[PDB]
Image 1 (tube, rainbow over the protein chains, first blue to last red):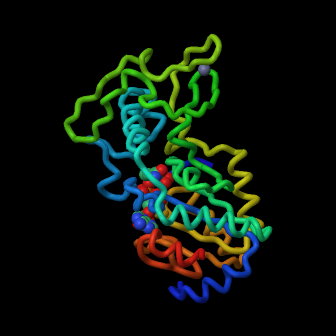
Image 2: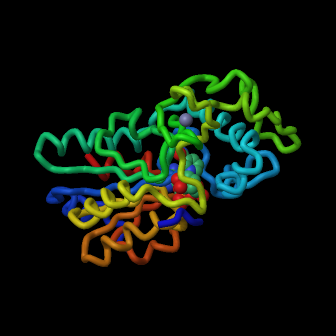
Amino acid sequence: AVKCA
Amino acid sequence: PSSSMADFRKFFAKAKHIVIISGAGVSAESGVPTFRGAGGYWRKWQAQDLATPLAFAHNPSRVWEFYHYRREVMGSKEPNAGHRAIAECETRLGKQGRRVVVITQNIDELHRKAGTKNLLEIHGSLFKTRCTSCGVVAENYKSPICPALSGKGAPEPGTQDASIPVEKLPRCEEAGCGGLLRPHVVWFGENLDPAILEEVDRELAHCDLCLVVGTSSVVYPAAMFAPQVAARGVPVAEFNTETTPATNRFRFHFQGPCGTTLPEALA
Ligand SMILES: NC(=O)c1ccc[n+]([C@@H]2C[C@H](COP(=O)(O)OP(=O)(O)OC[C@H]3O[C@@H](n4cnc5c(N)ncnc54)[C@H](O)[C@@H]3O)[C@@H](O)[C@H]2O)c1
Ligand SMILES: [Zn+2]
């Protein structure tokens, strides 16, 4: 799971 | 989305496993700015641009200045009544054999400073380093973290980059490494720790009450945590100064500074 805004 | 504190308290009285998800809003009343609007800037740059593998790879000095600054600011800071309510809640319920766990987006360690023991820091920590060569993670509270960063990190637009040479940025002190360190913080575009994500998953699956505190619910995948519990039929209570995109997913919404709403909520 990639940290995204 | 009720704002009935009494109805929340009924659930709180019976909950055996509470998950508390927190974002930058839980530390706002400690004097740590969020990234919403104004606090989302540092010099000319946006925080969400500096906190990226791209930015660090191409200019580790500017990014380190940015983290050094934050490390230094965080030095003076104290847990607020929000953090305290959360820590005190965990200790009191703990003696009843009930569980409270905090899952935080924050890297500021203020939950830890407040006494919270059951803590998952899903985005890492401002006060840890990781070596970009050997991968070793270490605690670091040094002020300054390296001599070259002293007096640096000034947030004012127009502040030229100290432009520290890479061998004088923080360096690994492991036997025979010498690698460049980076903050042990998950950047935008990076993977969260799979081991941490499985811990998060176990908590979300077992909990029976969830609070979502001071988070914008727009940073993924953390934004999907509370919606997932609420899908399972579990009560979710949101504590934030504003509504967010996730608000209508939740059973409760309590508007205002969490420092003034949490202590009553969690008594
Ligand atoms: N303190 C920190 O460690 C820190 C500081 C700044 C940014 N960050 C992270 C960088 C990244 C994006 O930051 P941000 O854009 O701020 O997203 P966020 O998900 O942290 O959003 C901040 C939320 O806090 C809210 N809020 C502000 N004040 C209060 C308050 N007094 N009581 C309750 N809620 C409040 C604000 O409305 C918003 O919903 C997130 O992972 C942040 O957690 C962490
Ligand atoms: Zn190393």
